Image 1 (tube, rainbow, N blue to C red):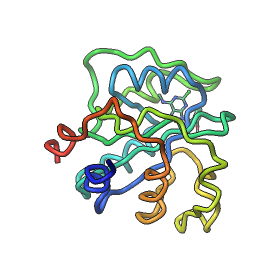
Image 2 (cartoon, helix red, strand yellow; image 1 turned 45 degrees about the vertical axis):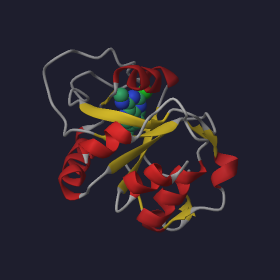
Image 3 (tube, protein in one colour; image 1 turned 90 degrees about the horizontal axis):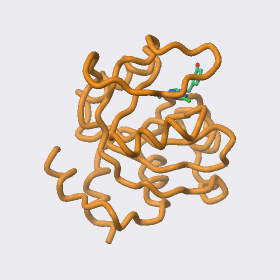
Length: 164
Ligand SMILES: CNc1nc(Cl)nc2c1ncn2Cc1cccc(OC)c1
């Protein structure tokens, strides 16, 4: 069903994450972690303290798709188990470094063709696929976008609800 998913998304905040490569999204799916640039790290930390759920919606550049979505379970933390991100040209490991723990809600893909009817008020009402890494998605658009994804029957939202 979709009832527990709707409960997790209630009064949530949503952020578009743009990854330059599939390898980083795969590593985030396997390890339950994400790292971003300091400007976005600051926005996510503020959002985490502000809302019952902060949802990251992932898209790999040039893929034409979203690759799933996850809920922050922590603020960013440094030190600890390092992460072998694939870094773009211009990208050093120091610029990442802050690591958020995340709980996946859906690891399934959604093609942009299916979200063409959803516009983001916080990005000039452009289609929600359009946006820089870290762009916030308004509540109603973000909720409807997450509800478009195919159900991921491998995930049990009971433990996610308990984190709240
Ligand atoms: C593990 N985290 C990430 N991995 C990857 Cl491959 N791309 C990311 C990540 N976070 C944000 N982006 C987008 C990006 C890429 C290169 C230069 C940027 O300067 C604005 C922005």
